[PDB]
Amino acid sequence: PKVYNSIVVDAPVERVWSRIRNFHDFSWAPSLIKSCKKVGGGGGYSVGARRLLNGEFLDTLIAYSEIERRIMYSMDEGPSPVSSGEIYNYVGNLHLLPVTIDDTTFVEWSGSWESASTEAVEYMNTVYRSLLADLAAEFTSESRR
Amino acid sequence: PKVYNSIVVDAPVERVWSRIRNFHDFSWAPSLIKSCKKVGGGGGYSVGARRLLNGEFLDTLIAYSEIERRIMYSMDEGPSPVSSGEIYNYVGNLHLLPVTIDDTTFVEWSGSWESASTEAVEYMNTVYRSLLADLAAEFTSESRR
Amino acid sequence: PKVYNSIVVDAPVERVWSRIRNFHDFSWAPSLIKSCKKVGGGGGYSVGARRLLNGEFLDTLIAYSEIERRIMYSMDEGPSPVSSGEIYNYVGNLHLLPVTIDDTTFVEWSGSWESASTEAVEYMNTVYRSLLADLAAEFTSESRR
Amino acid sequence: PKVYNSIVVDAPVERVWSRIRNFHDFSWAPSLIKSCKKVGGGGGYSVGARRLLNGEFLDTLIAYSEIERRIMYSMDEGPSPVSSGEIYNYVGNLHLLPVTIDDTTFVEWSGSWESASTEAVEYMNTVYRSLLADLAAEFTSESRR
Image (cartoon, rainbow over all chains, first blue to last red; front, top):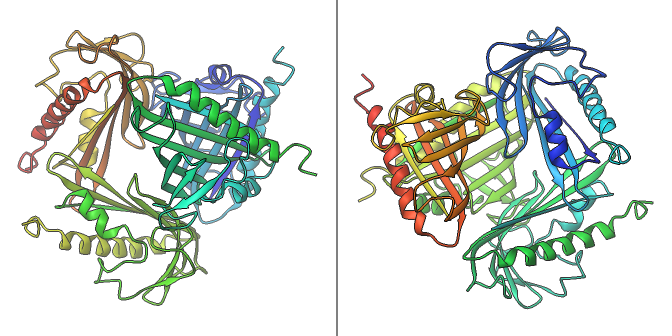
């Protein structure tokens, strides 16, 4: 199955990227993400780097693009209904584009995986919408004053 | 050289696509496009189809994606400073994405070409911004009532 | 689930493309494809075009790229284990690249779908390998004399 | 302008990738590359990493994909005719695909840049063909014994 969620953020793309570009800095989504621990070697832009979030999501960075402003990762472990016992080949894909007419930012987040069920679809929609909502709340049409 | 312009349109992506999806229907950008004539065989979604706009832009459809909502074309002839005597390998790339949180539409338009100069850069920025501005004006935050 | 199969064909990419580029001409894979009937409007390069193969595979063209030499389609109906009762969102993706050093052709064919099982994986591997094998047999290192 | 060169290598894709996957290890192309020095922070898979080759090519890693087996970089400095005084926005794109039928590897290398001339086209074709030729020579149809 797969999910796709997107929002427009009232801040220039360079600023939004500067904030989210580090695979080991998730401080920008404090609602859902309570802890983000580096695991394995490699820094925040090093493909192969890993992280553990909330003590239960284990992610590996599988692709990074400075030029396209994209971060892609596998979710290697997670809580039900996205545990490794119920899904496989989970790939997350977070990507920015400029909205040039008013110098804002389009943010898209895709997820896809294999599974015998669609049980995880609602759950990841909820997760991604929360993460994106934090990102938007940080860059408001008035927070840009 | 290349150009990139984008806007957010206050209408659902299915509606925006329905309006722009036909390579031979350019009625949605009346400010700059005064006439759009079919040239050669193939309909509005047929790769290889061609069109003449304003009696001076000759375009060929070189790629079309219903699934990705993308139209790509070569500009084979055009007025200075985008005539075939001054540039080559012009490719235009028009593409939609949904903004899911509020059910709006992100629209991006890219152009790239080869040239001894950048003289065409300002000119195409002006063209694309006008075309996109028509698209936005048609789908206003209030025109969605 | 998904499948991916590829081969190298001893013929220039322009020749291979010329042979496979028509969504309604499948005469190049006579082993598995016994009949290919046009369904609905639109010609062989018209996105939206449909075809029925062997009286049981119903395909729709969902993307076409002359510039990238790619054909993408949904399989809307098929025999078990790829019937619409057992899988959904089947997308096939057939794409050519030149092998420039000796002027040959790389051919890749991808398939992906959603399903409660992987039962269709072996089956589509078998189908794609047969189709590609026909393509190769037609363009041999000696058939290029 | 741009260049595109490709070859088929008689070795499995995992082996070819293992050999070329490190932005700071260029030992696989000894014909043209005599020295490869790390510059700046970040390791061989860290986007932002830089290198100096032959004391004259300064490259920065701008994208890396483990999942797609791709390395992309900007050439920030180089000898004429690819010096920063004569070209700009040089991007190199090195990418592997499996040839599944016989378990070999397709290798493609693209380059693109902006320039008032095409003088660099022949020159980069020559460079890329040499680099690829080293890669092939290392993995021969008999070196796989």
